Image (cartoon, rainbow over all chains, first blue to last red; front, side):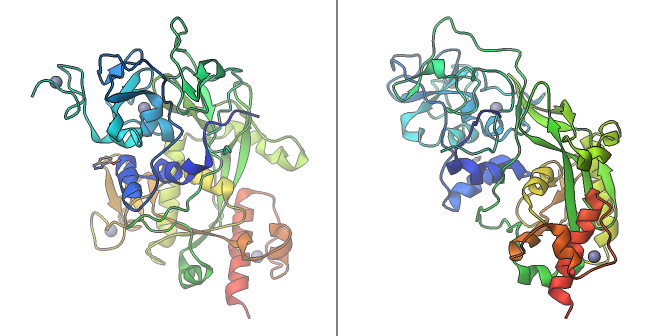
Length: 131
Length: 286
Ligand SMILES: COc1cccc2cn[nH]c12
Ligand SMILES: [Zn+2]
Ligand SMILES: [Zn+2]
Ligand SMILES: [Zn+2]
Ligand SMILES: [Zn+2]
């Protein structure tokens, strides 16, 4: 009964992060000890002629990015744990997230390490036009 | 190649929208093409779902610097015999809005304590995962009859986990700097630990030099067994599965080979007492 959501390649990392006091720190540490990034994300096929904004309603990858389903790039959604956000709600689930191609092998790690500019809508250090 | 960990137990026939699915496997077939997924204009997100996600199938086989191994060897367990606490859980089954996973109902320990929880699960929604009461029933059959009255005697998990920490602290503070849960066929005990255990690097207590055995979500602080009043999580427990020591057949048959003073009263605490007793007879008697 039921429908699988996960693959065996992710069992170890997700179990470790599902039990951690600090899930983001646990994922960072797991990678530093040689672990593989979380796979089985929702990667989109698109025209790569989008706005390049970080978090969007539909896929918006430019030629330097890939588009992913937002819940699939969120460690808290992937582990089914509390979000550290104000009322425990996610800012990625229900949106698409654009990730620089140079970082697309680890979308979950990318979203944990980076921040979106509220003025221009692009990732700080990966598109932000405010500096 | 798929696992049962985080299986979606809802009865919804279709998968999720690409922006809401946690994984590629969980996206509905209608969005899959050319090895990836597509956004389809006019096909909306689902803004009212509640999908129960199974916690059966955790794998604690990571090797991460500075994080202790949860599962320990027989030799290490023997040195820490004073920290041994037998643990067993009787479950109930998800029903109605979900099917296909086991929820903790009666948590039993070798101290003789049984605690009863409200049937609670991890329900994915459009905004988060809601840790909430779910529809459940005891498994069918005369051997699960005693669980029927427990379906209406449960305490909420925020209360149960405080009681577990207090019981372990009272039992172990003058016996050990840790706990070793002594298990028999550990899968469901490990699923139940998700409800009351946290892990991380080895820490020291907030009020002394002893290692931390408890954590508080109220203050994000750590405590040993002596300073844990009010704390809600067990932190960095250890454990061992006695069934892996080569035994054949069920717990009771192996326990009865060495002991006659523990009659089977068919309850979680009794299985927990028999598991610790079998491990003690195997390692320390003759
Ligand atoms: C996935 O790796 C990380 C998560 C959160 C913070 C940091 C900092 N470096 N790497 C991190
Ligand atoms: Zn999320
Ligand atoms: Zn900016
Ligand atoms: Zn202390
Ligand atoms: Zn006995």
